[PDB]
Length: 158
DNA sequence: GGGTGGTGGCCGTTTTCGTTTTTCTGTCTCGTGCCTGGTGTCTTGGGTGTAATCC
Image (tube, rainbow, N blue to C red):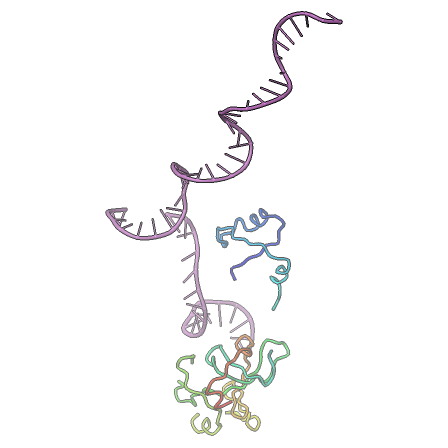
């Protein structure tokens, strides 16, 4: 970030390539690059099913999960979460007023608030609930699969 | 119903160039004293002076 490279053959060529630009610090702060480093400036640079992942988007941010099914297009990956639902207690959400999490129990939703499709698979307000676990189409940008440090609650649960 | 979009949330973040008194501290060209290698001055004695005559 903040570093811009221009491939020229003379210093004044770089000067005029960066001249006439207001998005450039007025200083001519330019440094040469070693032969080995030339290719190092253009180097471009772990998502598996059953991989423990966390969410960062919308209301369910910061919730660990399991990647369930990846779409053929390669942009959206299904997740297995522990729902955070209110059972119609205050329906008449964000990432700061959210109550705690708990696996879907069909009995509670039936008693308080529901189209049963298969055994354990419940479609509730556009949400997929398999065996009490939250299923929804999560965009790959919304999820973290690398560098996840499991917490105490995850050891207790996972 | 579903496409387009203001939106509230979330998320993380910088850059046009536009005064006063002292003591202590660290450089500073500048100077001086030194020094050593080419050189300085002495003085003896024999050659280079000199002088006549031969032949």
